[PDB]
Image 1 (cartoon, each protein chain N blue to C red):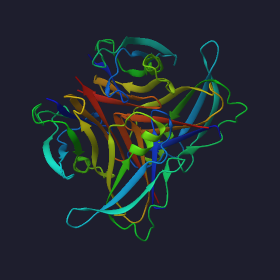
Image 2: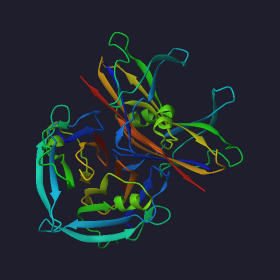
Image 3: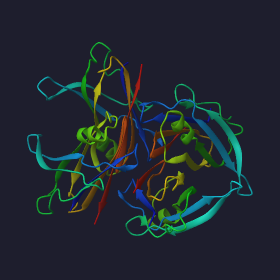
Image 4: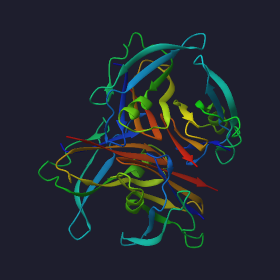
Length: 115
Length: 115
Length: 115
Length: 115
């Protein structure tokens, strides 16, 4: 599992459950091609997005659908999504965890890169 | 200015100077139409992006492009490119400050909304 | 002011107003000796804590006490109390801005050091 | 394991390895009593600090010795430590993870509280 997303909720002090995540890959013509998607589990984690074979070198965009998440919990948030763009596997294959910490008017996204 | 953007370097503890900022507004036909752009000043702030007249209700995107900033200072590499997407002015005109805190493998962003 | 403290509410996207701030300086005999204190203004900032004359080299601690702020507005509960410890002026006098971003189960702090 | 600490390094995009952590508990006389300590492992995690029996209701302080960490890696950081104070188990026993994200001039500490 070379690409994983983990989401925490700073209001509840909990994993962020059932948050939708959409991943895109930049195509040769500089448009965004859909690459993978899913929703976080009870642990706030989303596994199984891709395989080592398909997760080739490139520029990737991870979008975390935070607005829908907060609204469902009764909170009006600021952002539509949390988003981060990064280049992956340009020094060879690595495992990436995108760790997101969410508040209604703020977030952080961190890439934890191993192997 | 109803929209201000501030960029900070979390490695050096400094304003990030001469960082390119691009703002977009979402059209019907879900395409991001260019809205404003500029570069951060000595204080890491970018003022005068727009006016109250033109900054109407909508979904906006702020992209922080750091390449020229880190090349010039000679510093490493912020692999995480920030894109901050939000609805503005849906409850009336407000003053928005969008702050971005940059690290090589992370960024944080906060919105302060006044008035 | 060579030391400024700024407090933001990450749930509301607002300055945290009337937050009590206590600053200490570390003595020989590892005891924190009181140095300065005040409450944040409308802008969430606290200016005039000290002067360049008195703000000499040392280890300082900034404690952000939020109890009165959240009781008055009636808001939930920031269970994480912030304590920010740092050496100041060891490379000559600088201007320090200590920012704290508060959530119920998290906080973030950043230092911007100029001159 | 009711109290765990996990530390990430935003410069390296990695777990923060061999970071010292000191935990204190507020005594009846309002002084800080040493409670537990240890160092993070290769995963950036520190387990085994305490037991459910000994981790009673109270006010706890977690200190993460970040200065020593950064200096060892060749980076001059701003803070002496990252520190967070919180009340634990006042609604009954819970499991706490203190998730810390570190940059040289900024950090965040989040309490993830389960059970």
